[PDB]
Image (cartoon, coloured by chain):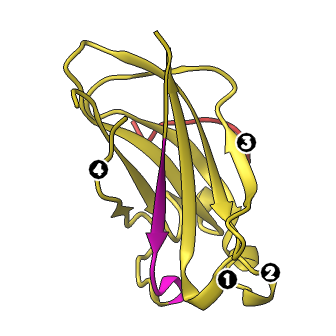
Amino acid sequence: CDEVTSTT
Amino acid sequence: KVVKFSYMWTINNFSFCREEMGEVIKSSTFSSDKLKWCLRVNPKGLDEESKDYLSLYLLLVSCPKSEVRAKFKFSILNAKGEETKAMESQRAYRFVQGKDWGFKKFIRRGFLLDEANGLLPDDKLTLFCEVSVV
């Protein structure tokens, strides 16, 4: 749940 | 050198949100102008994997430079204004104009929507974002 991601 | 700033976003009538999976609500823009930022939430997640979660991202809306690096932290405020359930970037991320970064699985809908947990006082969700640009 704590992973950083981007929508692109 | 170092610039640190914050934004509090109150989303009223949260329980009434009709956004389906993939639909987004964007906040008003904010700054520390030069740079303009906004928050964006998917009440029913970004995709099938995150359907059970709110997804929350920081978006760089306007940016004079090629890129900016920023660390960020998001939290939920309780009725006392205390931060709870915070998630933080472990390092700075590279933003360009129109780029977001954040948490696909920020908080479980089944937790947040149960009013006994105290995170929707008067049906309002209050998010707090802190950003640091170095």
* Left or right, B25 with reference to B98: right
Give the Cα separation between the discs numbered 1 and 2.
8 Å
Residue bearing the label numbered 4: B29
Badge 2: how crowded within 10 Å, few (<14), some, or many (20+)? few
Give the Cα separation between the discs numbered 2 and 3.
21 Å
The answer to whether the residue labelled 2 contacts the one labelled 3, judged by CB atoms less than 8 Å apart, is no
Which color has been applied to chain A in this rendered view?
red
- B119 inside magenta stretch: no
Instruction: Say which element carries label 4.
Output: loop
**Looking at the image, residue B133 lies above or below residue B124:** above
Residue bearing the label numbered 3: A2
- In the displayed orientation, state which residue is furthest to the front: B80
Chain painted in yellow in the figure: B
**Chain name for mark 4:** B
The answer to which of marks 2 and 4 sits earlier in the sequence is: 4
Say which residue appears at 50% left-offset and 15% top-offset. Answer: B2
The quadrant holding residue B116 is: bottom right
Residue type indicated by callout 3: Asp
Residue type indicated by callout 1: Leu
List x then y, in percent, for residue B50: 61, 59
- Front-most of B106 and A7? B106
Residue bearing the label numbered 2: B117
Q: What range is drawn magenta here?
A: B6-15
